[PDB]
Image (cartoon, coloured by chain):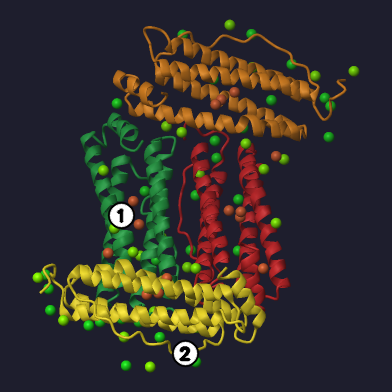
Chain colours: A green, B yellow, C red, D orange
C-alpha cells in the first residue's frame, strides 16, 4: 500500500530482504577471514586486508539493497546475521576456496532473484541486479579462482615459502 | 523498408511514437504547474522552479525517443500535445499528488512498452528503456512520494506556514 | 599459548569478544534506523543519514576490538549478530530515545569491561577503553540527549512541523 | 626535598632509574644485533637496519625517563649498561626470538612499574606509562611475533632462500 509502489511483487520484496541478509552474512565471513590472517600465528597482513576490503564491499552491497527496497516501496525486514561457518580458516588456500564457494553462493542467490524478477515481469529489478551485482560477482569469482590456481602452483598448503610469496606479490 | 531497420517491429515503432507524445504531455503538465506556482497569489518560487526543471527533463525524454526512432529506422509521427487536466493546481500538496500520479502513468507506459519489446524479442529497445527511463522514473516517484509525506507532516493543505517552510527548505 | 600474550586474562579475552558482538549489534540497530527514516512514508533523509553514519562508527568500533584481540594474542570468536529489537522506529523522538538507551547499554558494557580489566590488573586494556571508547560514548550520549530535549521542545511526537524543522536544522 | 616534588614516592623514583637502565640495556642489545647482521658473513642489511632503528627507539625511551625523573623532582642515578647476553645472534629467526623475549622483559618491567605507581597512588606516573610506553610495547611484541611466524613459514633456520626473501620483502 506504499504510495510509490508500482509493479513490485510481494515475493520480490521478500527475496530482496533475504538477499540483503546473505550480503551481510558474506560481509561477516570476510570479517572473520580478516581477523584470522591478522593473528600473530598466521600473520599474512596483505591477505588479511584483502578480506577486510571484501567485508566492506559486501556491507555496501547490503546497504544498496536497503535503499532499493525503499525506492520500490517495499519494507526492509532484518534477520539475525549468522556467524561464519568456521572460527579459523586454515591457510590462504583454504580461505580462498571458502571465499570462492561463498561468492558462488551469493551469485546463485542473485541469479535466483533475477529469475523471480523475470517471472514477475519486473524489468527495474532485473536491470538493478544486472547493473549493480551480477558483473561484480563474475569478476570476483574470476579473481578468486585465479588466486587459487596460483596458490596451488605455489605448493599450498605445504609450501610456506609459496604462501609468503603470494602475500608479498599477489595482494600487495 | 529503411536500410537501417533490423529487428524493429511495427508495433514497437508505433508504441515509441505514443510514448514520445506522453513525455510531451507530461512536460506540458509540469509547465502548467510552473506557471501556477509563479502566480502572484500563489508565489512559491522554489516549487515553481522544481516543476519548470521537470518540464525540461520530460521534453529531453521526448527528444531522446525521436532520436531512438530514427536510429532504429522507424518514423517519428507526432500528434497533438493535449493541454493539462487542470488549469490550476490548488497548492503544493495537490500539485505533488498530481505529479506522483503523472509519474506513475508515465512509468506504466514505459513498463508496457518494455513488455511489448520483450514479446517482440527486441533487446535493444529493452536495454534503452532500462538504461535511459525506468531507473529515473523510480527515483522521481520516490522523490515525489517523500515530498508528499513531508507536506502532510507539515499540515498541508491547511497549514500555510508548513507550505512556506517546505518551499524554503525542501526545494531551495 | 600465543607467543605475544602477556598479562592478558582469559576472562578479558572473552569479554572483548562479547563487547565486539555488542558493537556489531549496535551497528545493525542503527542500520535499521537508517532504513526506517529512508522509507517513503517517513522521509527524513538527514535523520536517516545520521543513523547510517552511526552504523558505520559502531562497525569501526567492532573492527578495532578484533585488531585489539589479535594484538594481545587473544582469539576473535564471533557469534550471531542479533536483529534489532524493533522493525519500525515510530518517529525521530522514539528513535533517538532508543539510540540513547543503546548508547547507555554499550557504555555500561565498556565500563563493566574496564572494571574487569582493573580487577585483572590490565593497564593496557584500561588505557585502550579510556582512549578509544569511553570519551566517544560520553560525547554520543550527550549529543543524543541534547537532540531529545530539542525534539520534546519541538512538540514531538504530535508536532510534525517540529519534526520537519529538526531534520532541516539539527542534522543537516 | 625538591621544590617541585609532589606525590612522588621514593620507591617510584628508584624504579624509574632501574627502568631507564633497562631501556639502555635493550638499546645496546639491538646495537649488537645491528652489528651482527652487518657482518660480511651475515649480510642482511635490511634486518641490520631494523635492529639499528630499534636501538635508537630504546635510547629515546631512556632519555624520556630521564626527563620524567627531573619533571617530578626525582634524581637520575645511572648504573653500568651491561653488555648484551650474546656476542653473535645466529640468524634472523634466532635474533627475532631474542628480540621478542627482550620486548616482553621490558614490557614486564613497565607493567611492574605501573603496579608500583598504582600501589603508591601516582596517577601521573600511571598515565605516563600508559600513554608513552605500554601501547608501543604491545605493538612491538605483535610486530616481532608476526615476523617470527613468517620466518618459521619461510623454513628458518635451514632455508637460506627463505631468510633472503624475508630480508627483501618484510623489512625493506
Ligand atoms: Cl505493486
Ligand atoms: Cl506492469
Ligand atoms: Cl504482490
Ligand atoms: Cl521479508
Ligand atoms: Cl536459524
Ligand atoms: Cl572452525
Ligand atoms: Cl558458501
Ligand atoms: Cl529468489
Ligand atoms: Cl525490422
Ligand atoms: Cl532477430
Ligand atoms: Cl513489423
Ligand atoms: Cl504511430
Ligand atoms: Cl482526442
Ligand atoms: Cl482546473
Ligand atoms: Cl496522470
Ligand atoms: Cl506499449
Ligand atoms: Cl597472559
Ligand atoms: Cl603483570
Ligand atoms: Cl588467564
Ligand atoms: Cl569468547
Ligand atoms: Cl540466543
Ligand atoms: Cl516493531
Ligand atoms: Cl538498549
Ligand atoms: Cl565485562
Ligand atoms: Cl613527594
Ligand atoms: Cl596525593
Ligand atoms: Cl617517599
Ligand atoms: Cl636509584
Ligand atoms: Cl653486576
Ligand atoms: Cl654468543
Ligand atoms: Cl630478555
Ligand atoms: Cl617496579
Ligand atoms: Cl621474490
Ligand atoms: Fe556481494
Ligand atoms: Fe562478491
Ligand atoms: Fe568485488
Ligand atoms: Fe519522462
Ligand atoms: Fe542493462
Ligand atoms: Fe519522471
Ligand atoms: Fe527526474
Ligand atoms: Fe529555517
Ligand atoms: Fe560503539
Ligand atoms: Fe587508570
Ligand atoms: Fe557510541
Ligand atoms: Fe559517535
Ligand atoms: Fe623501550
Ligand atoms: Fe619496544
Ligand atoms: Fe617500537
Ligand atoms: Mg499512504
Ligand atoms: Mg509481502
Ligand atoms: Mg539466507
Ligand atoms: Mg548458530
Ligand atoms: Mg555493467
Ligand atoms: Mg586479474
Ligand atoms: Mg532506401
Ligand atoms: Mg508500422
Ligand atoms: Mg497517449
Ligand atoms: Mg481537449
Ligand atoms: Mg542504469
Ligand atoms: Mg531523497
Ligand atoms: Mg606458537
Ligand atoms: Mg580463555
Ligand atoms: Mg552480548
Ligand atoms: Mg531472535
Ligand atoms: Mg585502581
Ligand atoms: Mg581521550
Ligand atoms: Mg553539541
Ligand atoms: Mg631547594
Ligand atoms: Mg629515595
Ligand atoms: Mg635492571
Ligand atoms: Mg658482565
Ligand atoms: Mg595511547
Ligand atoms: Mg603488522
Q: In whole angstroms, how far apart are the C-alphas of marks 1 and 2?
A: 47 Å
**As rendered, which of D152 and C145 lies closer to the eye?**
C145
Q: Is residue A82 left or right of residue D130?
A: left
Query: What percent of the width, then of the height, locates residue A48?
Result: 40, 41
Q: Chain of mark 2?
A: B
Q: Residues within 10 Å of mark 2 (few under 14, many from 20)?
A: few
**As rendered, which of C36 and A7 lies closer to the eye?**
A7
* Ligand 14 under 8 Å from disc 2 Cβ: yes
- Which residue bears the numbered disc 1? A136
Q: Are marks 1 and 2 in contact (CB under 8 Å)?
A: no
Q: Quadrant of residue B135?
A: bottom left
Q: In what element is the residue under mark 2?
A: loop
Q: Is residue B117 above or below residue D136?
A: below
Which residue is pictured at 65% across the width and 59% down the height? Answer: C104
Depth check, mark 1 against mark 2: the one in front is 2
**As rendered, which of A55 and B118 lies closer to the eye?**
B118
Q: Residues within 10 Å of mark 1 (few under 14, many from 20)?
A: few
Amino acid at each position: 500500500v506504499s504510495q510509490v509502489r508500482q509493479n513490485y511483487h510481494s515475493d520480490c520484496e521478500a527475496a530482496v530482504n533475504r538477499m540483503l541478509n546473505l550480503e551481510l552474512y558474506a560481509s561477516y565471513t570476510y570479517s572473520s577471514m580478516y581477523a584470522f590472517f591478522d593473528r600473530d600465528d598466521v600473520a599474512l597482513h596483505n591477505v588479511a586486508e584483502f578480506f577486510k576490503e571484501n567485508s566492506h564491499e559486501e556491507r555496501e552491497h547490503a546497504e544498496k539493497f536497503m535503499k532499493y527496497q525503499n525506492k520500490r516501496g517495499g519494507r526492509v525486514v532484518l534477520q539475525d546475521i549468522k556467524k561464519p561457518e568456521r572460527d579459523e580458516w586454515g591457510n590462504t588456500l583454504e580461505a580462498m576456496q571458502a571465499a570462492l564457494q561463498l561468492e558462488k553462493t551469493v551469485n546463485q542467490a542473485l541469479l535466483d532473484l533475477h529469475k523471480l524478477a523475470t517471472d514477475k515481469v519486473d524489468p527495474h529489478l532485473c536491470d538493478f541486479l544486472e547493473s549493480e551485482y551480477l558483473e561484480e560477482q563474475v569478476k570476483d569469482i574470476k579473481r578468486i579462482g585465479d588466486f587459487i590456481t596460483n596458490l596451488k602452483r605455489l605448493g599450498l598448503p605445504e609450501n610456506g615459502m609459496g604462501e609468503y610469496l603470494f602475500d608479498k606479490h599477489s595482494v600487495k
